[PDB]
Amino acid sequence: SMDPPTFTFNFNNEPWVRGRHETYLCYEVERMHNDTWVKLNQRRGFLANQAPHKHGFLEGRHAELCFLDVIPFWKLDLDQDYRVTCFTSWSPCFSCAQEMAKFISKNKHVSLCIKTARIYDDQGRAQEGLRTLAEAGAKISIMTYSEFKHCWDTFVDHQGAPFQPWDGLDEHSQDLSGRLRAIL
Ligand SMILES: *c1cc(O)c(O)cc1N(C)N=O
Ligand SMILES: [Zn+2]
Ligand SMILES: [Zn+2]
Picture (cartoon, helix red, strand yellow):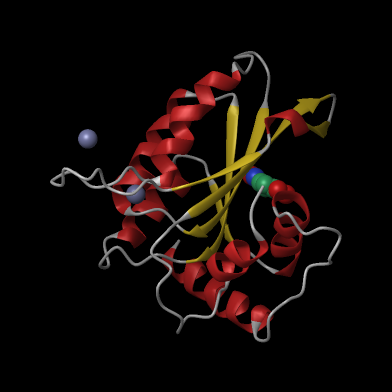
């Protein structure tokens, strides 16, 4: 679980704020059991991108790559159907999106849903990767109030405090979902 200030700073969907250099990724798994999706709450977690190593030269490992690194250790049953949801503060850069597309193509027991607080630019070339991820079968969408509240409730050390939406949450979300539709 996550510090409240850490959630609030990072999942803020106002487009004019800066300094959100990190990407946070919260994940949940459901298994299909006879027409309903059943939550596997023992599999839930979150992670962030890694800082580059002190030696320089190589970039820090991206959260999306870390996430893919971890799935094999869940030891999912290849004969079963699973729905994996990521709640991401930024959407993936191009190279991560392509890696993700490749992953889901090779693992057809996994349905991927990425719900993103904000769209990451990746100097224009990120739009292409989001189209590639959608083509390989991933559902990509913008976090609304429902997703933000769920993530607060589920992944934050809230100590019983309810999710408090920031001013503009809904409008920013709606602006972003129009952008994403254009993109896809
Ligand atoms: C993914 C994740 C999620 O929570 C819902 O409700 C639906 C999806 N979909 C539709 N994936 O294809
Ligand atoms: Zn190193
Ligand atoms: Zn990346």
